[PDB]
Amino acid sequence: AAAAGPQVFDVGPRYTNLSYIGEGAYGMVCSAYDNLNKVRVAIKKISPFEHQTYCQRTLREIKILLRFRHENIIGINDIIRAPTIEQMKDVYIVQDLMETDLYKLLKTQHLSNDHICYFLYQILRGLKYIHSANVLHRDLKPSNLLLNTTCDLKICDFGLARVADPDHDHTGFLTEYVATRWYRAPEIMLNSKGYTKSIDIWSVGCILAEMLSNRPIFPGKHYLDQLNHILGILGSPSQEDLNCIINLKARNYLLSLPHKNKVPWNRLFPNADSKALDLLDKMLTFNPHKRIEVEQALAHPYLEQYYDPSDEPIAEAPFKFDMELDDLPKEKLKELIFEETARFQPG
Image (cartoon, rainbow, N blue to C red; front, side, top):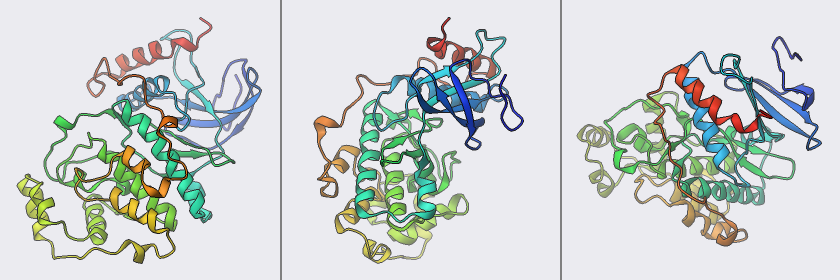
């Protein structure tokens, strides 16, 4: 087997000449030379089988990414594993090589308004497809937006994704949540499980704000801090918006807070394009029912140079889990992973 900073990075005959590119979630990533396609590719070594949580995220992601086919969503090119369940200790996922991501880019580079507009377009174009498959990404953030040298953007990391389930979105006040804190919609802390499409639009509005200023708009330091960052800028919710919250505990928490007025977007972002700020406002709307949906966002004047619904494809059918994953044991998920990855074997 070939080695890299030991550990074993063994990707068959096909993928030669390895170069390390940091640590991912459940292993380690390298670029490698793909001898079939004669391009460098990215390969993620994944060793999830010792934990149920890692297995779940790995399966969810493989099933979704193999089914999706979209320019603005990262594809799985290949999956390398042992030929038997017994011998499978790791899985390697091969994907197009992308040089950077928006998180890294924003650490050092100011974006032109043109770059902001094009990146936002591509985010929403990809998100239209995801939502059209009845899937919620649920962890959109700059580090899950991959970028190449010619500004092509692809959404990645579907480990927290779920099929949308608006009828079962309700939960009590202060219900714990897994997805990245700074990109969480206000309702997550109030009454929502994040099972509706509006959760993702909030995250995109956070990303647009971060593109405009190079800093996170709501950098909460802990769970409830996140909500008071949001309220610090949006100001106190309206009576109408509070009446929509029937959860007494959540409503009474909001009523206990001193009145705060809205911070004008042009104050926070004095250099920004006015149309960008109008779209921003509609994405960062407190009441998820009034929040803009992905197809409206696409049609917003800010994006008029790119908008073309005929060139913004949708999924051929909704996505559905045969088995609901949360339940399943480690060993069962490993079996499902083996079956899902069978198509890439010479066999």
